[PDB]
Image (cartoon, coloured by chain):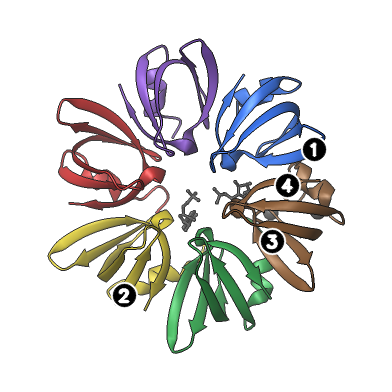
Chain colours: A green, B yellow, C red, D purple, E brown, F blue
Amino acid sequence: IPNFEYARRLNGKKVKIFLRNGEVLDAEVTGVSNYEIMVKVGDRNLLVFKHAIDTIEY
Amino acid sequence: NFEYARRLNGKKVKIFLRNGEVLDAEVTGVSNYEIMVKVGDRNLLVFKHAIDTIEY
Amino acid sequence: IPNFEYARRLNGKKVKIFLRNGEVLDAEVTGVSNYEIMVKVGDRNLLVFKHAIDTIEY
Amino acid sequence: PNFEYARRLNGKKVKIFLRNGEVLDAEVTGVSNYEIMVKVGDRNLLVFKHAIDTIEY
Amino acid sequence: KVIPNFEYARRLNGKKVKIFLRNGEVLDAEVTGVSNYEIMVKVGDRNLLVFKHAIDTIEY
Amino acid sequence: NFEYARRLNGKKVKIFLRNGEVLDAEVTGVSNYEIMVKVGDRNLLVFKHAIDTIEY
Ligand SMILES: Nc1ncnc2c1ncn2[C@@H]1O[C@H](COP(=O)(O)O)[C@@H](O)[C@H]1O
Ligand SMILES: Nc1ncnc2c1ncn2[C@@H]1O[C@H](COP(=O)(O)O)[C@@H](O)[C@H]1O
Ligand SMILES: [Cl-]
Ligand code: NA
């Protein structure tokens, strides 16, 4: 388990999450754990596994 | 090692799998690497590595 | 809680293993380690890496 | 635990089903935590375990 | 480990590189940070967090 | 932990990547997660997770 990750400072930000299948989420980040990012996308709440993310634009 | 996935135990969720399948699931258990679910009359062990997103 | 997993509880059971490539194994589980599942499928003996498994129906 | 079922395969003839759909008719010559060393035909290969789906033995 | 284990990627911090992602994209990138799990880059006028698991190769 | 990959340093090898590309490579360094190579007139950092097999 890493002690430092840049993903932590994404909390509360509006970002673009590029998923490994080619979909993109216009997301607001509501939580970050070592392996998950929690987001709101429109009216949906999602848990996103980091392993399913390629890049995040912020 | 805090995880949000553990908060989902007992809840109805939609699990989006890496192959494109979507599970209309009730979460029955969560471990470090697995999520146990009921889907219809099926009982499944789902590996987290095979999950992309979960809608809850 | 260290090393707790549900997969080892499938030991000795008949299960359906859904592999990441879309193949499905009608399997009898004979052993479970941290990263591997040992199974019998018909007359074949297989080592299945957990990373290659999507779901197991039991 | 310091246990791997893959270690049972050392020195054995096996079929390795890779994630890309290829199958290796392999003789296992070594097993590390992350790799399986094999002879296939006249070739020596390092096979990463993460690229393996199943092994028939 | 507070002092990182050796990795070649940290030598690329501050450099211009081409990152080849698993999805077939190439990023013309300036590396601005490296963690255990991520590589931070500037691409055009975009700021990206790139997960190492999504990278195949880096040409430098 | 033991890595067979360390033994490949300085050798000419064929690296079969997960996307189907094949690198005709000279290995110039090996770390826990990376293999550094020369291919043509290019220098590449290759993540081990992107490699399927290496012929050597
Ligand atoms: N220590 C942990 N605690 C909780 N979940 C984990 C842990 N390690 C890995 N995971 C999850 O399991 C997936 C597969 O693990 P790995 O094969 O180690 O990458 C990860 O991408 C996470 O979603
Ligand atoms: N402690 C670490 N030091 C350097 N790179 C790492 C470390 N942990 C993970 N990585 C990289 O991040 C990738 C993530 O894969 P995984 O750990 O399997 O989710 C690995 O394949 C490595 O390239
Ligand atoms: Cl650095
Ligand atoms: Na650390």
In the structure shown, which secondary structural element does the residue marked by tag 1 occupy?
Answer: strand
Amino acid type indicated by mark 4:
Ile
Mark nearest the camera among 3 and 2 is 2
**Left or right: E25 as drawn, with respect to C36:** right
Towards the viewer: B50 or A8: B50
- Expressed as whole percent of the image width and height from the top left, the position of residue D10 reads 42, 16
Q: Nearer the viewer, residue E12 or B6?
A: E12
Front disc: 1 or 2: 1
Residue C13: image location, x then y, percent: 15, 42
Residue B10, given in percent of the width and then of the height, sits at: 27, 74
Residue type at mark 1? Arg
Q: Are marks 3 and 2 in contact (CB under 8 Å)?
A: no
Q: Which mark is residue A4?
A: 3
Residue type at the position of mark 2 = Val
Q: Which residue is mark 1?
A: F42
Q: Residue at (76%, 47%) from the top-left corner?
A: E9
Please say if F14 is above or below C21.
Answer: above
Q: Is residue E34 visible?
A: no
Residue depth check, mark 3 versus mark 1: number of the one nearer the observer: 1
Residue at the image point whose x is 82% and y is 34% from the top: F41
* Residue underneath mark 4: E58
Q: Are marks 1 and 2 in contact (CB under 8 Å)?
A: no
Answer left or right for E52 relative to F11: left
Frontmost residue, E34 versus C33: E34
- Amino acid carrying label 3: it is Phe
Q: Which residue position is annotated with label 2?
A: B13
Mark 3, ligand 4, within 8 Å: the answer is: yes
Look at the numbered disc 2 and give the secondary structure of its residue: strand
